[PDB]
Image: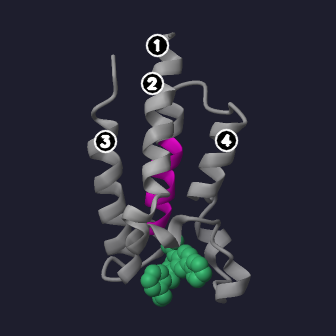
Amino acid sequence: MGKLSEQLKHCNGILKELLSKKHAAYAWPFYKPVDASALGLHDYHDIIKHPMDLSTVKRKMENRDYRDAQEFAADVRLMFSNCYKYNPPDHDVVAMARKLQDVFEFRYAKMPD
Ligand SMILES: CC(=O)N1c2ccc(C3=CCNCC3)cc2N(Cc2ccccc2CO)C[C@@H]1C1CC1
């Protein structure tokens, strides 16, 4: 019933959509934390100080870590920003990030208030 609750319901709906099969073709790189060691990315944690991914956002939502929509959105955008910072702009993953961020931003804009 509360404003913060309702807005976080909207955030949770968005999160569910981002993780859904509908968007899997471009969402998959963002499902789990970047495993720098697995991918041979030995500079990743020197360049990306605050890693983020959708599983972490999900855990934080489930743990009631996010106190408002703004805090949730900051993590989702951090995830995209990290991708844009680390990868060259012509990399496949950047195109995927842009597409998933489009999904995010347009639905986030429909926030109840
Ligand atoms: C999230 C993120 O920035 N990354 C990213 C994150 C996760 C994963 C994987 C997830 C599941 N297992 C396979 C790899 C792969 C990437 N890639 C590689 C990747 C992405 C998409 C298409 C093709 C490739 C191959 O060049 C890039 C980048 C990394 C350079 C930071």
Left or right, 45 with respect to 13, comes to: right
Between discs 2 and 3, the one toward the N terminus: 2
Q: Which residue is mark 2?
A: 7
Tell me whether the residue at label 3 lies in contact with that at label 4, contact meaning CB atoms closer than 8 angstroms.
no
Give the crowd class for mark 3: few <14, some 14-19, many >=20 residues within 10 Å. some
Residue at disc 3, secondary structure: helix
Q: Which residue is mark 3?
A: 107
Identify residue type, mark 4: Lys
- Residue 26 location in percent, x, y? 39, 71
Residue at disc 2, secondary structure: helix
Identify residue type, mark 3: Arg
Q: Residue at x 63, y 56 (%)?
A: 55
Tell me whether the residue at label 2 lies in contact with that at label 1, contact meaning CB atoms closer than 8 angstroms.
yes
Q: Main secondary structure of the magenta part?
A: helix
Between discs 3 and 4, the one toward the N terminus: 4
Identify residue type, mark 2: Gln
Give the crowd class for mark 1: few <14, some 14-19, many >=20 residues within 10 Å. few
Q: Residue at x 68, y 83 (%)?
A: 42
Q: Which residue is mark 1?
A: 3
Q: Which residue is mark 4?
A: 60
Residue numbers of the magenta segment:
74-84
